[PDB]
Image 1 (tube, chains in turn brown, yellow, cyan, purple):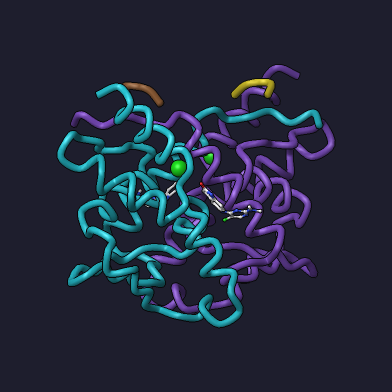
Image 2: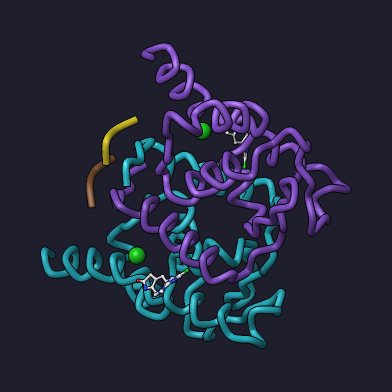
Amino acid sequence: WVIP
Amino acid sequence: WVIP
Amino acid sequence: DSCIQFTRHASDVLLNLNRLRSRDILTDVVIVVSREQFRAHKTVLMACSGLFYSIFTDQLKCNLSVINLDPEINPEGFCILLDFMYTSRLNLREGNIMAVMATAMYLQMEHVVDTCRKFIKAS
Amino acid sequence: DSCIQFTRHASDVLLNLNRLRSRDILTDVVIVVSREQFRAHKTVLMACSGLFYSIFTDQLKCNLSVINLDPEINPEGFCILLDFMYTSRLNLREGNIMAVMATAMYLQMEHVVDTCRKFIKAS
Ligand SMILES: CN(C)c1ncc(Cl)c(Nc2ccc3c(c2)CC(=O)N3)n1
Ligand SMILES: CN(C)c1ncc(Cl)c(Nc2ccc3c(c2)CC(=O)N3)n1
Ligand SMILES: [Cl-]
Ligand SMILES: [Cl-]
């Protein structure tokens, strides 16, 4: 999971 | 396009 | 094999499937969550959820145009997860994380359950 | 928004759609190319091809279960492109590049046409  |  | 690969292809496919959903094009099922109705593509639901995968591979349920979820399922939690299915983006907030995790456990969306467990553990 | 994103989600969705195709699950159309028949999901075809997008948004053609391609279309070229649609992987070879480019131009798959033009220019 990432900060888009 | 890439070499997978 | 000796194949070449287009990096953005999967993302572009998902973006177009979401465009079809937003325009209600070739949607083939309505998911009923309490009073709320959500139109979607059975194939996308199966690709994202262990629960929908089991439902639509069933020789009788595969032909249903309406699926009613358990009355305990929260419509907002379902909406956030349906958006995630079609975008890879999860709107996880303090006020919805419990409903999102419970809905993801019911829908069998393992990666969402994992990030909810981690975000809850941090707080 | 304040969304988080699961990097592998789009790829995982496409992988599962290809698993459904390989098992012939919820396929809703057969594409006829000369003597050859290819089963697929209309939504995936639309998401990948300008030609299928136009066909299945048509109020009459959207309901067809069989689509016949132009007799000039090569079945192997179509097969390679259908595989690309469901995998992001293109089996581009010296012996098939002309048939692949011609099929991609007909199907309106701009990124495939672009890599074929570049590979031909290099030789
Ligand atoms: C497991 N399998 C062969 C498969 N093939 C095709 C599809 Cl559409 C599919 N989808 C599915 C099944 C289980 C789970 C998911 C999708 C997401 C998840 O967390 N569990 N799973
Ligand atoms: C253009 N548009 C709004 C849109 N929405 C939904 C879908 Cl499924 C779609 N697909 C499509 C259209 C044109 C092209 C492609 C897909 C690939 C391409 O090279 N051209 N295009
Ligand atoms: Cl997930
Ligand atoms: Cl393309």
